[PDB]
Length: 124
Ligand SMILES: [Cl-]
Ligand SMILES: [Cl-]
Ligand SMILES: [Cl-]
Ligand code: NA
Image (tube, rainbow, N blue to C red; front, side, top):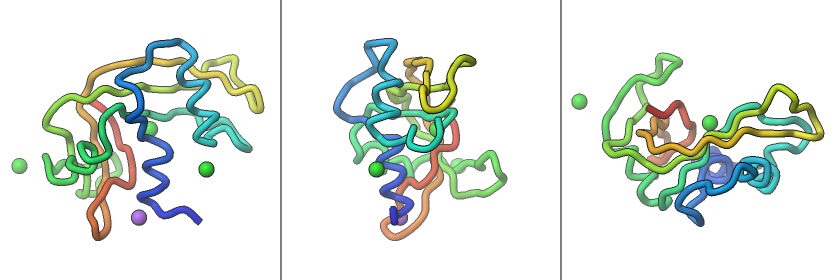
């Protein structure tokens, strides 16, 4: 039974690469992080920064989350991210994703002690 912090790491952290360099990145990563077991997760963002740099966002700019909660934080600097989105032809179990690499600010919701990211809200 995964903790919220561990689920965030599994779904969103990829410090092993600086950026997605292939159109197939999302297909491979969505599968290896077990996000296509039982259903295709329709949208997911991976962050290519160190875990410490992403945890540090919980001490940066406090902003509202999309849902109206006030425990969201926007990174002061841009970060390397990859957006993974199902294509229109995708359907379980042959999940298919479009890979879009970008450099953007990230917005995360933080909770707990230690106070760490538990939800990826958006990128700007
Ligand atoms: Cl897993
Ligand atoms: Cl996401
Ligand atoms: Cl402020
Ligand atoms: Na947690």
